Image (tube, rainbow over all chains, first blue to last red; front, side, top):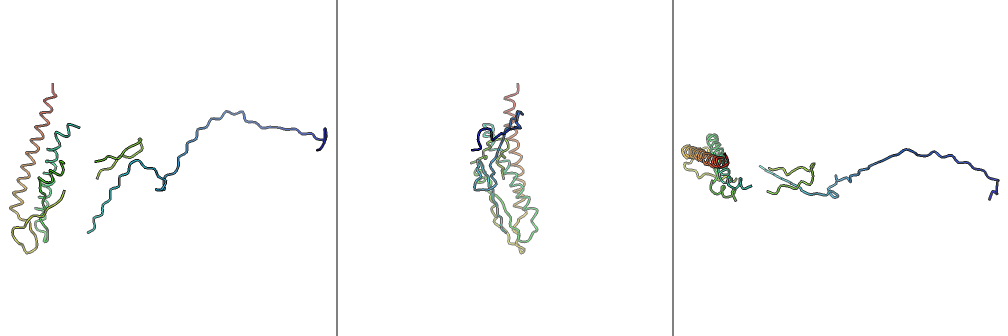
Length: 50
Length: 123
């Protein structure tokens, strides 16, 4: 569109030459009883009405 | 464990004797309370019941292990008091002495069994 020679451009690049290593651990929240997965549950209930 | 099965009967008898001893001493202590009923346990039936559970499963280290947590029969009154107290001194004094004697006998038998199991091993 502009024509040969009717355009000039120059590019400079800031690069990344730093070696990085990352380990990510994520736990799904289980505070709601509906999405909570259980292995063992002990429920002792006592009601001594006088 | 097999060691528990051998000593289960005497341990349960000793514990039941201690519990009934506490109940009899409570009957003695509350002799003067008006309206107090003298309570007791049937030793043989409760010993059957104890002689005749599911630890919750621990998947890892953080998982918390399961946390752990008798029937009293009224004594038939002999003399009618006016304040409603049915505790009789003589009957429960004899029962108290008998329970003390049987607790000592159970201690003797359990100690003899443990001492025999020990001299089998010593050498």
